[PDB]
Image (cartoon, coloured by chain):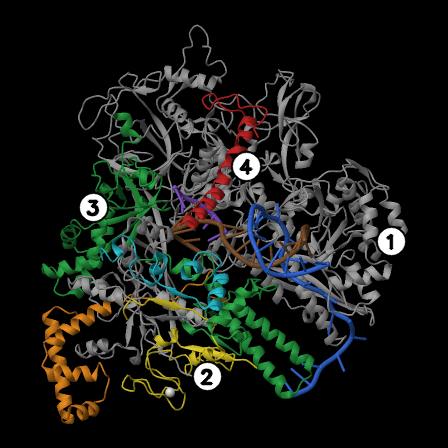
Chain colours: A orange, B red, C cyan, D green, F yellow, G purple, H brown, I blue
RNA sequence: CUCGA
DNA sequence: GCATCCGTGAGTCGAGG
DNA sequence: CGTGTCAGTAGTGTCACGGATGC
């Protein structure tokens, strides 16, 4: 039916990264206010996407230790974000 | 070339029907060639650039 | 050949460029404009930069 | 002229055999994208139909070679593969071009580089830029020669990230995220903040056609109500700008070097004379000369 | 009085010349063409009194040309007859609402004739839903009113050209035989004194090769062309000889690659030029040949085909023209001059209207079905065949669908104001299929031709790249069934003007001489001067005896278009500003309330009625019930007809189309009278603007070269306030992970933004919405594998599970604000047929009330345009002696340059209409008012007047009216006989040192408002391929820093500003994001990177077998975050 | 990626250079599947050749997470990086 | 395609 | 050795389809 | 899977200028 070279076809667009850049900046600020253990666990679970046992194998710690560090560090980030007015 | 008959009336007086019709000949082609003359002008300009 | 291919006869310049295997020293206004360098003119020359 | 061609292949060390191809490269798909349409159907670049026709005829030639088909079919097939690659690289160069649906000539790979619509002139010599706007121009006699009046609504979006920065500094907004929502919603605090932002931050005004360098000049922005751009009456000669519906573009220099180039090199008050003749341009020209 | 025929308001005309013929139907061009196409009873009765015997409609003509269909044997036959239509499928407004096509089903009678079985089965076969033309002269395709534009094409016939050679500098000649359909044939004499012929663009054969192939002996050729030495040199320099030799020579150049048989070329050389299958000269094409060659000029037009005699007479016409001959008679033919043709002359340039343009597409669609018929005959059995089985209507309806859907002549209707719509329907376009390409049109096709007098307007035409290619039909002009444009003239018997009026074509006009409309004429009819200004063939104007005038013009405005005829004092404006005045009148915006102009021309009445945006009474009667919703008329016979008002409807261009009743309850109204008027209409007249009090003076520089100063009264009293309506639309589809649903529940949105929504997620009627407000709340399910690492962490640190949907709601675009006036919902669940893959569709209509703003573009009727530079308070405005402030301050400098004195004369007459006048009746009628009608000697304040084009008020009478202007309520005359008045500076109080010209001028609000034309962008969407910002305001894109603008940066030496524009501010993928972070962080602007567009250029040069590499200073090639594998 | 590199060299592309660039041959003439929107294997949009449609998402659907970064899938032959590679990975047609 | 400078 | 014919180029920006 | 009474183009009003192409 259509050809992109042919007129009358809308060109593909990509939105700006403003909202993503601002979220990344706020995440980086709340990340700096975390302990080296908690920061090096959320950056290995969400930034590197590993499994719970993968981070446990890397850091040389227990399985539940990674579960507990992630469980608190998440709430610690929610504390810092809600203290700065980040929308739920 | 100029028409062997001039537009004797002034715009204050008011041109006749035929005087107006013969005036539009040069008026339209005056606007018509201005687009082509600007095209060759901008073409010579970007060659000089 | 980059300043020429953007002027006129794009295919005619690109053919002779690949045949002669010409290498372009990116030191010119039109070239640095394309690649994003500071133009070697005005505030872009090494004296003021 | 024959030596001109032969000597190049001799000295350079590249064989002339490259003029005959055994394999043709395929441009990555995102440069020949196929988009979906709101009617359910699809639409692909003409390069895909040219690549598809080369693939179709090359696979049929592989069938004829395997089957031992008569030399008349194989040779007449090899001819069509030549015309297909010729269409992929430069359709229409030899003979009549490969028409698509509706007798439209398909755009070849070389068509992406040719002329005003080519890659060089359309996307390299000139580009579309962020931090810019456009509106109708209106004469402003009260303005000084180094000043221009731009609408408040234009300045807010033009200085949006700077406004968000000051909204979070003065604690009108908790975080930069809500500061963005405040500018998008136009909370009344931004108009007091925006005045602090545009202070002595020059902007560039432009009216096409940009014939000479004074077709773009720098000005000091002044927050004015309304939706029109207020231009100084003396720079009207440089822009060749009358006020019968004209529009001008505004560009905001961001870096410190760019603002300095506008403050010193491009300021309207520092460019009174014509660079072509040395005689002034920002002088009484119409009503002003009659008044004097 | 002016136009005392429908019951209109009494506008008093400054008319010294009577109107012999009243303006025809301005919509006849679109109407009559379509009535002939479908063979309506009105067209048939019109042709009946026209003298026609057995007339045939366009559809009947297609069916007769097609019938019959036969195979090679003749054992099977199919025929068609009796085309008829059932009632229309859906009303006009229902099609606009549901986005369908206005059409009526077409029935025909088809039958199969079997010669080998002797029996026939006849029945009725439905052909297809046929698009119907509305009463307003428009079609409705998918709910949008479109206009089929009449096309100017080269008429069929034989045409001759006198070209000058480039190298030898000798006068050459060429011939073209352009058929109405089929292959082309062009003879020519090159610079070597030899004659040749190109057949269907193919190779140029010697002219005797064609003569030998037709069966002409080499002796009879010398007998016919012996009087010229250039033909003796042609038969001598000829290569091959023989009847069966040159016939194969033509075969191998026309159809290469095929075995040449003496009868395979004998077959095509008969079918390509002499069989009605693959060649046809229309009745006009045959007639144009029978006149150009001077043969069969008496025989009834029965030959629909080219003949061999015509080919010989054409070569005879050419060879005589080459060697200076000026006269020729074909053997057995009438005498005819030997000359070259203009091809721009309106006798050789033909206009095809709506019916023909549709008929040709029907003809092509029928031919595609005919091939299906012949194929279905030889496949199916010869006894179970019915007309239903042989007919596949798919290519037929798809051919008319292809036409109305995609065509340069099927155009999106201009709907700024009623005048723009009427002008668009009367447009004559040279562009399009069969006409010419814009690249293939020189400065000769576009300029004015002397045959355009009274046929196409020499003023109304765009000034852009389409100048000359698009014209407007003259007022009194019409189209004959041949395709040429006729214009009426007054037949002068023996130097005596007669009321007998006859329409003449272009070449018919050249065979006579006509007198100018404003000729001094005796009350009996005899010309006052022996010598009168007379137009002659080839555009010659000269005096000539009164006993030589054959005809004369009907009206002075006979040469201008309807919009051009609406400019008062047009004879005092140059053609440049007059063009802009007519082009900008079509750009006027329908205001909230409309005022008819004080200074008019009389054309405003008929232009408004014929436009079709008012409501005229069909039959005489009384008003039974009147409401803002509908008007009911009780006829004399007893029947009732109710007209429904179109209230606050969006036009094609966002303007407000709003009709309002005029009559009240119990008002006797005649037939054809305006009972209600729509946009830009006041009491039935075109009200494109308002009457504003104007002062001609510079004012503190705020009106500096074409700038305009306005009184704030125009804002407080909604004088230049207009209504604008925008259409917003969104749909809920089926996606890969579920289905988009329209719901009020939107993730992470407060109950405050959703407060203006109902329970469905739709904004409620009446709610005022700014930009960014939610109109339709739609959510789309997004997959888990599509989440950002930060977004998945942000989802974990907020505990909000089950939010697998994202926000894709319909929000208000930047720059929009107004009241929601209407909602339309379409749901697949509720039997509404949506495109496959859609579950819900919502359309929201938002209306804004736009007051006049700073920068809004105003203009007059004389091409005097300008933007609003300053709107001062009412007290700041210079006010007259009695305190009434002026409304608009126009600069004086922009008046004597443009040569548009009409605005000055309108200002004078505008005040005289505002105040009134009384001529001194004592001691007789003064010497300046002797020519004025007695109705003009006394005028009341706010009187309406007409200044017809090339007639109307003269400066002697206008000067006399200023001397007797009526006093105000206090009894004081504010303006002087000069037309100037004493003004007071509202800012200081001191009176202005000199009197200033003050009056009333008609100003129009053009559709160029800052509310639309303002735009700005920090960041936003980027084009996916080039990674550069989008274009256009609607796409929220940035401005384009073009090639010339980069030269300006380099001329300044602003290197860093140039690098900044071309990198971080454009297509630097990582630079733009780090710049935005550096701004919100308060850091410094980082260093620009490499443009992504340059990466694409390299990757494209690679696809062209070019090994491009970037080398460092040492010489090693460096990659760009990529590698290469094999 | 600094912005100072002196020369930009152009030359004839050997048929062997075309293979050095190409991440695989485009055998079939098909484009995609007009239901699943998944590109057909060895087609003009093959993910084994040019790259994944979505980031870290393969064709056969076995590897959809980021933890398997850089794995060449054995069942569909697609690498697992971002779709940015679909703007720079070249293909080629081997002529008979 | 159509229009604005 | 020269007339022919092919290929090259033909202002900038903006708005709605 | 196999196919078979002839089965016949689209589209047609730019131009200046230089130099390789061609009888
Ligand atoms: Zn896989």
Along the line of sight, the residue nearer the viewer: E1073 or E319: E319
In this view, which residue lies farthest toward the top?
A: E923
The answer to whether E206 is drawn above or below residue E912 in the figure is below
**In what element is the residue under mark 3?**
strand
**In what element is the residue under mark 4?**
loop
Q: What chain does badge 4 belong to?
A: E
- Marks 1/2: CA–CA distance: 66 Å
| Pair 4/2: label in front | 2
- Marks 4/2: CA–CA distance: 62 Å
Do the residues at discs 1 and 2 belong to one chain? no
**Dot 1 corresponds to which residue?**
E216
The answer to whether E845 is drawn above or below residue E963 in the figure is below
**In what element is the residue under mark 2?**
loop
Give the image quarter of residue E42: top right
**Dot 3 corresponds to which residue?**
D220
Residue in the picture at 89% in, 54% down = E217
| Pair 4/3: label in front | 3
The answer to whether E789 is drawn above or below residue E309 in the figure is below
**Dot 4 corresponds to which residue?**
E457
Disc 1 packing (10 Å; few <14; some 14–19; many ≥20): some
- The answer to whether residue A6 of the structure is visible from this angle is no
Mark found first going from the N terminus, 1 or 4: 1
Q: What chain does badge 1 belong to?
A: E
- Marks 3/2: CA–CA distance: 59 Å
Disc 3 packing (10 Å; few <14; some 14–19; many ≥20): many
| Pair 1/2: label in front | 1
Along the line of sight, the residue nearer the viewer: E828 or E430: E430
Quadrant occupied by the C terminus of chain E:
bottom left
């Amino acid at each position: 039916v259509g050809s992109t070279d042919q007129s009358g076809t809308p060109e593909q667009s990509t939105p700006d990264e403003v909202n993503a850049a601002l979220d990344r900046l706020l995440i980086a600020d709340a990340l700096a206010q975390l302990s080296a253990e908690h920061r090096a666990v959320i950056q290995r679970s969400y930034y590197r996407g590993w499994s719970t046992a993968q981070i446990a194998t890397d850091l040389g710690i227990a399985e539940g230790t990674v579960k507990s560090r992630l469980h608190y560090a998440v709430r610690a980030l929610r504390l810092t974000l809600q203290e700065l007015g980040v929308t739920r | 070339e100029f028409i062997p008959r001039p537009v004797k009336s002034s715009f204050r007086e008011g041109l006749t029907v035929l005087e107006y019709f013969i005036n539009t000949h040069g008026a339209r082609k005056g606007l018509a060639d201005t687009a082509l003359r600007t095209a060759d002008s901008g073409y010579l300009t970007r060659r000089l650039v | 050949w980059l300043s020429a291919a953007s002027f006129q006869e794009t295919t005619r310049v690109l053919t002779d460029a690949a045949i002669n295997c010409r290498s372009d020293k990116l030191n010119g206004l039109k070239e640095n404009v394309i690649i994003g360098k500071l133009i070697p003119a005005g505030t872009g020359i090494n004296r003021y930069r | 002229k024959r030596l001109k061609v032969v000597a190049a292949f001799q000295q350079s060390g590249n064989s002339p055999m490259g003029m005959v191809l055994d394999a043709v490269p395929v441009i990555p798909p995102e440069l020949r994208p196929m988009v979906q349409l709101d009617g359910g159907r699809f639409a692909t670049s003409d390069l895909n139909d040219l690549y598809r026709r080369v693939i179709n005829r090359n696979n049929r030639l592989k069938r004829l070679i395997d089957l031992g088909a008569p030399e008349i079919i194989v040779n007449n097939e090899k001819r069509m593969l030549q015309e297909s690659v010729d269409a992929l690289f430069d359709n229409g160069r030899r003979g009549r071009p490969v028409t698509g649906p509706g007798n439209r000539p398909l755009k070849s790979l070389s068509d992406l580089l040719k002329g005003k619509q080519g890659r060089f002139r359309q996307n390299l010599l000139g580009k579309r830029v962020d931090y810019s706007g456009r509106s109708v121009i209106v004469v402003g006699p009260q303005l000084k020669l180094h000043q221009c009046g731009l609408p408040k609504l234009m300045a807010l979006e033009l200085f949006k990230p700077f406004v968000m920065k000051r909204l979070v500094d003065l604690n009108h907004a908790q975080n930069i995220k809500s500061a963005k929502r405040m500018v998008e919603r136009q909370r009344p605090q931004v108009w007091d903040v925006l005045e602090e932002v545009i202070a002595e931050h020059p902007v560039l005004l432009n009216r096409a056609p940009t014939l000479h360098r004074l077709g773009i000049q720098a000005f000091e922005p002044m927050l004015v109500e309304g939706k029109a751009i207020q231009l100084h009456p003396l720079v009207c000669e440089a822009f060749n700008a009358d006020f019968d519906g004209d529009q001008m573009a505004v560009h905001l220099p961001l870096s410190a070097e760019a603002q300095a180039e506008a403050r010193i090199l491009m300021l309207s008050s520092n460019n009174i004379l014509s660079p072509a003749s040395g005689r002034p341009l920002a002088m009484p020209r119409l009503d002003m000369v009659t008044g004097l | 009085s002016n136009n005392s025929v429908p019951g209109a308001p009494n506008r008093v005309s400054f008319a010294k010349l009577r109107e012999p013929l009243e303006v025809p139907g301005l919509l006849d061009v679109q109407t009559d063409s379509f009535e002939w196409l479908i063979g309506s009873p009105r067209w048939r009765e019109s042709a009946a009194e026209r003298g026609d015997v057995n007339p045939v409609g366009g559809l009947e003509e297609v069916l007769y040309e097609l019938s019959p269909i036969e195979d090679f044997s003749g054992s099977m036959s199919l025929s068609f007859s009796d085309p008829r239509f059932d009632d229309v499928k859906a009303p006009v407004d229902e099609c606009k609402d549901k986005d369908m096509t206005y059409a009526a089903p077409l029935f025909v009678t088809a039958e199969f004739i079997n010669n080998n079985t002797g029996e026939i089965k006849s029945q009725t076969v439905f052909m297809g839903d046929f698009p119907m033309m509305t009463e307003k002269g428009t079609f409705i395709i998918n709910g949008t009113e479109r206009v089929v534009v009449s096309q100017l094409v080269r008429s069929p016939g034989v045409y001759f050209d006198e070209t000058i050679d480039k190298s030898t500098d000798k006068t050459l000649h060429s011939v073209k035989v352009i058929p109405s359909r089929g292959a082309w044939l062009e003879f020519d004499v090159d610079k070597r004194d030899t004659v040749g012929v190109r057949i269907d663009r193919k190779r140029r054969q010697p002219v005797t090769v064609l003569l030998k192939a037709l069966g002409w002996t080499s002796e009879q050729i010398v007998e016919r062309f012996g009087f010229s030495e250039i033909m003796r040199s042609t038969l001598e320099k000829d290569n091959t000889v023989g009847t069966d030799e040159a016939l194969l020579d033509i075969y191998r150049k026309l159809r290469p690659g095929e075995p040449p048989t003496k009868e395979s070329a004998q077959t095509l050389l008969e079918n390509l030029f002499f069989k009605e299958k693959r060649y046809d000269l229309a009745r006009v094409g045959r007639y144009k040949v029978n006149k150009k060659l001077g043969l069969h000029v008496g025989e009834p037009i029965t030959s629909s085909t080219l003949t061999e005699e015509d080919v010989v007479a054409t070569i005879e016409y050419l060879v005589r023209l080459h060697e200076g001959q000026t006269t020729m008679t074909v053997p057995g033919g009438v005498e005819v001059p030997v000359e070259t043709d203009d091809i721009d002359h309106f006798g050789n340039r033909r206009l095809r209207t709506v019916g023909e343009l549709i008929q040709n597409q029907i003809r092509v669609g029928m031919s595609r079905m005919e091939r299906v018929v012949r194929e279905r005959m030889t496949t199916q059995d010869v006894e179970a065949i019915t007309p239903q089985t042989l007919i596949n209507i798919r290519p037929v309806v798809a051919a008319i669908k292809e036409f109305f859907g995609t065509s340069q002549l099927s155009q999106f209707m201009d709907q700024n104001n009623p005048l723009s719509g009427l002008t668009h329907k009367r447009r004559l376009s040279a562009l399009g299929p069969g006409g010419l390409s814009r690249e293939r049109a020189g400065l000769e096709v576009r300029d004015v031709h002397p045959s355009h007098y009274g046929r196409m307007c020499p003023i109304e035409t765009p000034e852009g790249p389409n100048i000359g290619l698009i014209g407007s039909l003259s007022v009194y002009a019409r189209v004959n069934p041949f395709g040429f444009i006729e214009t009426p003239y007054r037949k002068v018997v023996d130097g005596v003007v007669s009321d007998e009026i006859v329409y003449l074509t272009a070449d018919e006009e050249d065979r006579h001489v006509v007198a100018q409309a404003n000729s001094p004429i005796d009350a009996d009819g005899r010309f006052v001067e022996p010598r009168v200004l007379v137009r002659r063939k080839a555009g010659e104007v000269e005096y000539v005896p009164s006993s030589e005038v054959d005809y004369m013009d009907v009206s002075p405005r006979q040469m201008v278009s309807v919009a051009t005829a609406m400019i008062p004092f047009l004879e005092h404006d140059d053609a440049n500003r007059a063009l802009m005045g007519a082009n900008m009148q079509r750009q006027a915006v329908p205001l909230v309330r409309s005022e008819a102009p004080l200074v008019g021309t009389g054309m405003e009445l008929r232009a408004a009625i014929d436009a079709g945006d008012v409501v005229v009474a069909e039959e005489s009667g009384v008003i039974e019930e009147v409401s803002a919703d509908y008007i009911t008329v009780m006829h004399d016979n007893g029947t009732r007809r109710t007209y429904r008002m179109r209230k606050f409807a969006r036009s094609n261009h966002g303007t407000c189309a709003n009709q309002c009743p005029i009559v009240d309850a119990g008002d006797r109204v005649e037939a054809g009278q305006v009972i209600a008027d729509g946009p830009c209409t006041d009491d039935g007249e075109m009200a494109l603007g308002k009457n504003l009090l104007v002062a001609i003076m510079p004012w503190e520089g705020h009106n500096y070269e074409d700038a305009i100063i306005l009184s704030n009264r125009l804002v407080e009293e909604d004088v230049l306030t207009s209504i604008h309506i925008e259409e917003h639309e969104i749909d809920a589809r089926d996606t890969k992970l579920g289905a988009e649903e329209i719901t009020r529940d939107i993730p992470n949105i407060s109950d405050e933004v959703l407060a203006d929504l109902d329970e469905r997620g739709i904004v409620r009627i009446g709610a005022e919405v700014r930009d960014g407000d939610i109109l339709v709340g739609k959510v789309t399910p997004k997959g888990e594998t599509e989440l950002t690492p930060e977004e998945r962490l942000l989802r974990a640190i907020f505990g909000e599970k089950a939010r697998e949907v994202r926000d894709t709601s319909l929000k208000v675009p930047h720059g929009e604000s107004g009241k929601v006036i209407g909602i339309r919902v379409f749901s697949r669940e509720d039997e509404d047929e949506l495109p496959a893959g859609v579950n819900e569709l919502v359309r929201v209509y938002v209306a804004q009330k736009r007051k006049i703003s700073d920068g809004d573009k105003l203009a007059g009727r004389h091409g005097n345009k300008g933007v609003i530079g300053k709107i001062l308070p009412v007290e700041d405005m210079p006010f007259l002696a009695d305190g009434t402030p002026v409304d608009i301050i126009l600069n004086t400098h922009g008046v004597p340059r443009r040569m548009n004195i009409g605005q000055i004369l309108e200002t004078h007459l505008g005040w005289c209409a505002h105040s009134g006048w009384k001529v001194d009746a004592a001691k007789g009628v003064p010497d300046w008012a002797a020519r004025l009608p007695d109705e003009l000697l006394e005028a009341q304040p706010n009187a309406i007047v007409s200044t017809p084009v090339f007639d109307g008020a003269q400066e002697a009478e206008l000067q006399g009216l200023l001397s007797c202007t009526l006093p105000n309520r206090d009894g004081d005359v504010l303006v002087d006989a000069d037309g100037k008045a004493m003004l007071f500076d509202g800012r200081s109080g001191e009176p202005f040192p000199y009197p200033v010209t003050v009056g009333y001028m008609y100003i129009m609000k053009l559709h160029h408002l800052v509310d639309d034309k303002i735009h700005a962008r920090s960041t936003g969407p980027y084009s996916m391929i080039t990674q550069q910002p989008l274009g256009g305001k609607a796409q929220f894109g940035g401005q384009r820093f073009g090639e010339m603008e980069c030269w300006a940066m380099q001329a300044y030496g602003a290197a860093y500003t140039l690098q900044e524009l071309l990198t971080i501010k454009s297509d630097d993928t990582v630079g733009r994001v780090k710049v935005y972070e550096a701004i919100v962080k308060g850091e410094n602007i980082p260093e620009p990177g490499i443009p992504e567009s340059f990466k694409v250029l390299l990757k494209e040069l690679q696809s062209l077998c070019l090994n491009v590499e970037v080398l460092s200073s040492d010489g090693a090639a460096i990659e760009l975050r990529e590698g290469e594998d094999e | 990626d600094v912005n100072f590199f002196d020369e930009l060299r152009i030359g004839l592309a050997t048929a062997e250079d075309i293979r050095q660039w190409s991440y695989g041959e485009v055998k079939k003439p098909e484009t995609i599947n007009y239901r699943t929107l998944k590109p057909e294997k060895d087609g003009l949009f093959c993910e084994k050749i040019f790259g994944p449609t979505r980031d870290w998402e393969c064709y056969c659907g076995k590897y959809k997470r980021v933890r398997f970064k850089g794995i060449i899938c054995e069942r569909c032959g697609v690498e697992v990086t971002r779709a940015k590679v679909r703007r720079e990975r070249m293909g080629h047609i081997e002529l008979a």
